[PDB]
Image 1 (tube, rainbow, N blue to C red):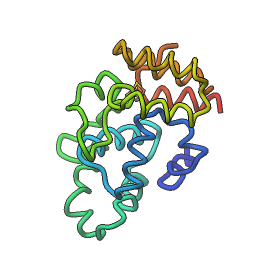
Image 2 (image 1 turned 60 degrees about the vertical axis):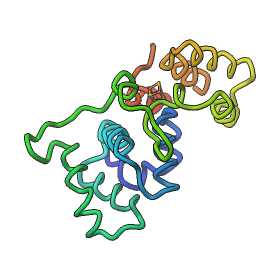
Image 3 (image 1 turned 120 degrees about the vertical axis):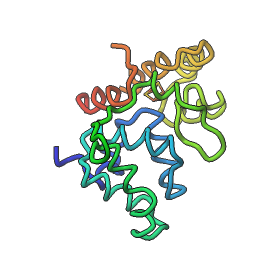
Image 4 (image 1 turned 90 degrees about the horizontal axis):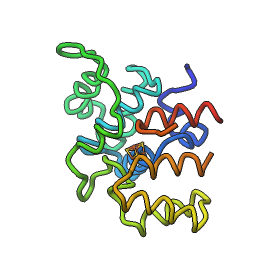
Length: 181
Ligand code: SF4
């Protein structure tokens, strides 16, 4: 669909369907005009999964890395992004990451936005985000209980149900949310 493009992915109509990890990656990208490696990978493969074309992805990434010149973007990042679309080397059209894959990556440190917020954020940070999403105190306690147990995809599924099958892939969360929209 032509509805998913370099500009629409920043709009509320599309972004309201993102799970917490993708919202966190978009926030880091908008604040810093950049993402570190694992965040570039997690977000670019998710956007490929929602239908962002290779041409639109290059527009998205070059526009989002707003503070560098197009020549620096082309020298330093274009190959990596094209490679994610199966346009380089062996031309493997890499699949988007599921939660299992996301969780397997090195844990995020200072300045990183990849990973899973249900594992990576403090209960203080999660509670504030869930309050902003209109969840009640009882609902927040239920989500945090799943987090404490290490059941991140269950916490994420609870947030999906509370804000709208077990979800264990950010692209499935997006697709299910978009179909209900
Ligand atoms: S459980 Fe999966 S889709 Fe949900 S925020 Fe974590 S990594 Fe993203």
